[PDB]
Length: 341
Ligand SMILES: [Cl-]
Ligand SMILES: [Cl-]
Image 1 (tube, rainbow, N blue to C red):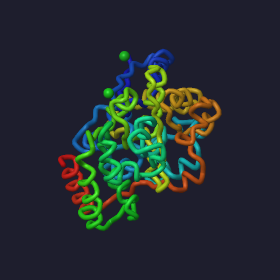
Image 2 (cartoon, rainbow, N blue to C red):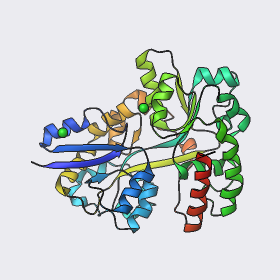
Image 3 (cartoon, protein in one colour):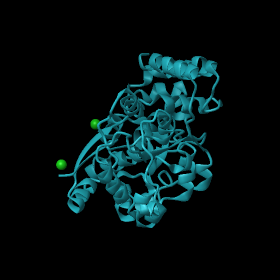
Image 4 (cartoon, rainbow, N blue to C red):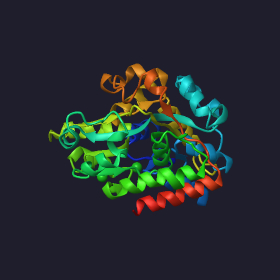
């Protein structure tokens, strides 16, 4: 009896994907979920993960490769690798040279999710929902406190977003940028932030319990769809702000000590099927990395410029870089100050 252990982000697969794979292959899948790159990286660095497949963001995988925690993918066992978009492969290869270890799964941006009606009520019809000003100017966040604010519990993403907003290199190597301006601004915003969390904000936006969030694009579009299906009158939207935003590429990778390698390759080749992954995108509102799948994706998802953004918006996106120990120290120390402010 073959088994397969998979660790993926929460809210990142269609409801029937695993069952359909089990039915086709006779493999039993053990599926577990996380909402933090830090949790996954900690598990990878502390010992065996016990998983056959894990799904880091590519910028985290970039440094994880150098610790030897992954084994290279046997492309001879991934015949339809060909379906993957070559331009996305090239971007991911900046993190994973020659695409040896990582299979691109989904990608999106770190932007602003918000309740349309509540934000306009508080900040007026002309609320700047196209700008990080909406949530990174203290005067606006003090007012939005009235209906609830959440930030992601994602330190590398939040500091890069703040640095970009301040006109600094999103990947600044100047320690003073973190300890000075970035911390100063975050500590001014902190009293108005209800919580730091990277998954509770989906249902809280959908149900009207918060009105604005730093969020991952497809998560917010899921919240919007859950609100529509509830017929609760909640109108949620998402913005890639005008100052730019961070892009991420989530990738499947195989732990070096994976027990069930043959089954893992079966699952990866299953995900490379254009109809399988288009069906996932249809349900999670994330762009997949599979060029053959794009026309199969629902018009609702494929034509949303907050999911598949056009070239002029993609040109404004930035990605995370590896930092040295000093910046890791000052960034992490500053993050701890902010979450307890
Ligand atoms: Cl099962
Ligand atoms: Cl929840």
